[PDB]
Length: 246
Length: 246
Ligand SMILES: NC(=O)C1=CN([C@@H]2O[C@H](COP(=O)(O)OP(=O)(O)OC[C@H]3O[C@@H](n4cnc5c(N)ncnc54)[C@H](OP(=O)(O)O)[C@@H]3O)[C@@H](O)[C@H]2O)C=CC1
Ligand SMILES: NC(=O)C1=CN([C@@H]2O[C@H](COP(=O)(O)OP(=O)(O)OC[C@H]3O[C@@H](n4cnc5c(N)ncnc54)[C@H](OP(=O)(O)O)[C@@H]3O)[C@@H](O)[C@H]2O)C=CC1
Image 1 (cartoon, rainbow over the protein chains, first blue to last red):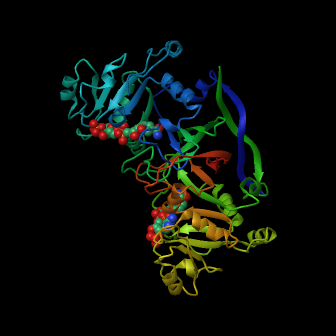
Image 2 (image 1 turned 30 degrees about the vertical axis):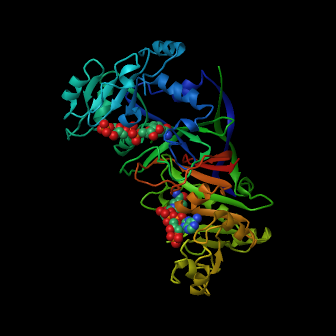
Image 3 (image 1 turned 120 degrees about the vertical axis):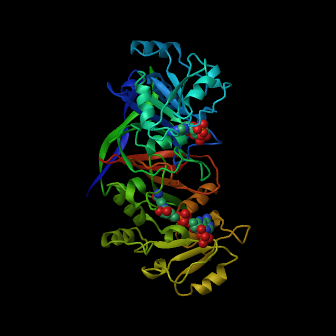
């Protein structure tokens, strides 16, 4: 008559002061966290973007995770982003933690082919980082002189990005608390290379049908077990989950 | 300082007697329930099947949902299934509910092109139903004489299946409590045609990377809101969710 199953139910209302402890980074070491939203049937997009599906809670969560991060890493696909916005209180919180007032943005591109004309370069407090390959880093540095710091992230193939090198290059610059929000190609590479430490996933209570892509894309296939650290909900039936690599 | 967020936690251990009430069908009317499993990053398969990812709880849940159903509807893709197995106690439970001892199997095929040589026809207590189009129903009836009951499920196009007609044809035969377990093409059609009443989804705590398909496939795009009826968990960090159409 016994089963391994237990009913979950809401046991505690969270104040905005208790949220940071549920999502804090470790005290030490580098930590790469992803934060994505998807539908129940695994779809990442509605009309080409993720925004349509966001829950009453998602803005507390998405804004908190940006506030906690040293750097937000984004793929060049989804940039096409502006400078991350921090409000007054967010800046104060960051300072009290000894971080910069606003997190750095880091754009991953294998080819380095970003035009000087982009909002990631224009509407922003801080020169973004461009993470790219050894093969193209010098040319890219020259082309983006003044607009971005360009960093070579290659492993044994100077024509590709090694995602473990990428994470160590950020940590070498004091950016060890890393957040990524997209896109699916980038996330797929972190998952394929087994460098993703934690996935925060908002499960939106919709089905969207078969057209949408998943939150990850690409040829990778892995089977990486994660531990469920927490599940939050709201009155709208969204689940805000946090899973950390076992 | 207040947020819409609430922490979920386990509040009640479920006995196998309490599970049926969490998953019961309505008293009246037809009800189409889906039961699927997917990874955290929205992948439906590991090495081409769903079985590798199943949780300690999934066998209580998958077996219960089969036990409760009048008919299990499956697409011809994933059949390539045998007769659903019911143990002694499952048969007793069904009888006490006034149902057949074993649920019917119903195979959906647009072309009707199933060979007489299949385990769905061979290793089974009960002739399965074949749900197909008006255009091909008579030929199909003759070819499968003795092995299956063939039912025309077309709407205004005699060359296609109308999924609402499909559900009413089952209900007309006393099979109003319907379960589907696959595959993604079929599920995508139920979602696209807005005839899916409830989705029971097991969220497995793995990431699998970008190669896998979603639990639904096909060109459909919808935005159908569902209410979260419950979330169960186990010690392995699986979530067993039940969402019902709002
Ligand atoms: N559901 C959700 O939460 C989210 C949805 N989205 C969505 O992301 C979509 C667009 O994303 P998409 O362009 O497909 O994916 P990506 O943002 O990840 O970027 C694809 C491009 O980014 C670069 N890139 C990514 N990753 C890597 C790597 N490891 N090494 C080198 N280069 C890399 C490549 O740049 P290059 O070609 O220059 O070499 C590549 O062409 C949008 O539809 C947006 O809505 C995005 C994030 C969150
Ligand atoms: N993660 C999970 O829980 C699950 C995973 N799986 C998987 O399903 C996969 C195979 O499934 P797949 O073949 O792609 O999909 P389907 O089982 O849904 O079937 C595709 C075929 O089934 C028929 N079919 C489906 N739906 C309809 C409809 N509304 N009208 C008419 N005909 C229809 C068609 O038959 P025809 O061509 O003859 O006309 C079609 O070619 C496997 O990989 C299996 O592991 C499946 C279910 C659960």
